[PDB]
Length: 198
Length: 197
Ligand SMILES: Cc1ccc2c(c1)sc1nncn12
Image (cartoon, rainbow over all chains, first blue to last red; front, side):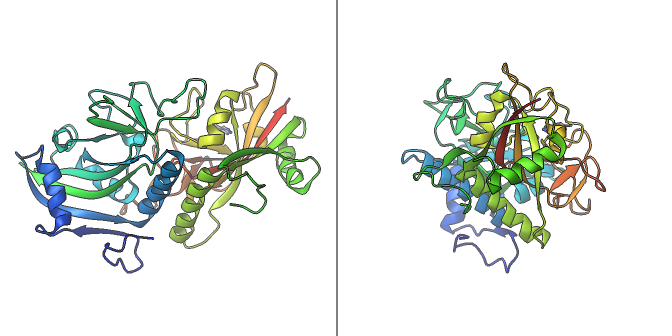
């Protein structure tokens, strides 16, 4: 079941679809971005239609919904990256083995921001040769989360006496989360690519 | 959920001890004894992990479509320490969990063609009581190439398309003895053999 609102991809498995401003789908992403990035301007927003990534992500979403007690397991988050990474993320998603060490490390995993502003820093969304910055808008299975720790390679157990019964993700602060870290493949779907400039 | 699994009372995870001398136990024992006939089998357990199985079959179906054929699966061995057994049973193989074992063909999970390679103490580390642990694993080796140190994913098939990757890497493409996979849910742990020297 690929979402019915996607463009027909004609038996092909990947497509980047450029959105039209004035449509709700474009305007809602612009507003979530501009709420903390008013100093920047969007060149374009592309919807990522990746059938394999969607299938694997929605399988993990279904399992986390079954495992957790009627939780909102999914957040819409931002990820700034450099241009060299964009073809790889587009095709293969977020690979923790490729992840930057974050300035404040709450674990060795893939980082995702509540605020576009955080992802808009040049450290993440490194401007390319043409001054273009790249930011993903990402469905993330944050699930049940705890404050992380720089040493984590997996999320911590909820209970030290049950080592395999893990939290889903970790955050910088559980009362005001600004960051989430995930430690497993297909726990994040890159849904949109915002291309933007100063 | 495979026919040869036994009922789980609507539960998602069960380890099920095989009966000695029945067909399923005999098949798995023979794979091990081919190179480990000098070892002693305490027991074999079928890992029934619905979640792991479902993500693996999804990845299998994707690879069968992409490779345009259905010879992507191999049966391989993985030795591990007793303290890693609960994690593998519940969450499968994880490339970020890898201490002072060699990663000379890349930073992925290592699987052996021969049980005797997994039977080494450096991999199947004997516990206090001399008990060693080896998994029989369904691995999506798909299309493979020679590996090398420092790989985080397998190499591209053609560098004119950097994103079309090989499925796995090996030590030797003519006569492979190990495979490394770089993604979660490319490996399903199907049996656990508890044994001693
Ligand atoms: C280089 C290397 C590293 C780990 C490893 C092998 C070979 S064969 C095997 N069976 N379980 C673990 N491993």
